[PDB]
Amino acid sequence: EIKYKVITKDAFALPYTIIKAKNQPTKGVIVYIHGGGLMFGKANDLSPQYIDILTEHYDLIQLSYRLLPEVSLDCIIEDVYASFDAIQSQYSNCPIFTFGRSSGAYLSLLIARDRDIDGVIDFYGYSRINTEPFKTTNSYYAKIAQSINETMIAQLTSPTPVVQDQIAQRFLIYVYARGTGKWINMINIADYTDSKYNIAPDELKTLPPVFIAHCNGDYDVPVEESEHIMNHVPHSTFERVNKNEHDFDRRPNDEAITIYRKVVDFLNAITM
Image 1: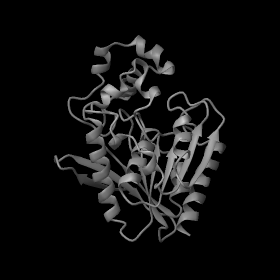
Image 2 (image 1 turned 180 degrees about the vertical axis):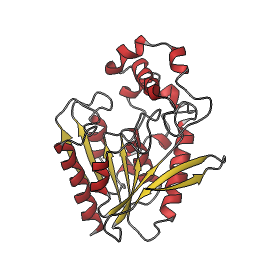
Image 3 (image 1 turned 30 degrees about the horizontal axis):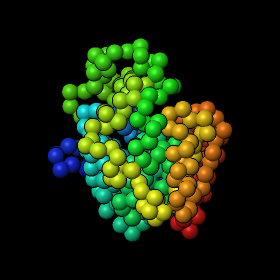
Image 4 (image 1 turned 60 degrees about the horizontal axis):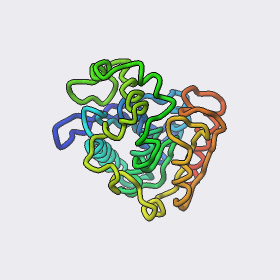
């Protein structure tokens, strides 16, 4: 693991790590964007086992961005693109991919629209925020959301922006947000319906190939968000996992490993 940083316009350090391809030279660079509903998480949240599969022949770069609610989604997008551009310049003549999980896959798809890359790996993400499941109360999160209060939640935030959880239970900010339907409010942008944040059909149509893995019974991001992408993009591969889970790869079970190996196959076809 090798550490770098990108210095933002506002003089904030965004760390990123590069893990090098095991068998050299690299076939490509995979820019990894972690999940956490834009509100919690950390860049180094991938199991070692997944990293070993991905980095056999690819470099894996784990990027960071400032989290909600201490910054807005406009700031997140700015951090992601500043980190992406710093990484892309370092791989000038080389295939490059975005790989996100959950909200990281959303960020990975924005990069795919606004930069020129060779493919996207979308694990249980989405291409838009202007959708009813994100606007309204989420059933799965509602009970826990109702068992905390706003002071409880405000004290899980940081007095200044962070790129990873500063307290173990920061994730309750996200449970609260989904469970009360305030997640769009906490994104804190002027107009969440704007095409900046919602990839248009004509834009989806021009995306590079997309690998999608999504559980049909996902309680956090409906599987329809993946079906929506498949309604427009020209090249897709879809693993539609028959589970009532969101992060089906939380543990490196055999089914999860198989999907990761399929990811590499998808990359190999592209870089051949």
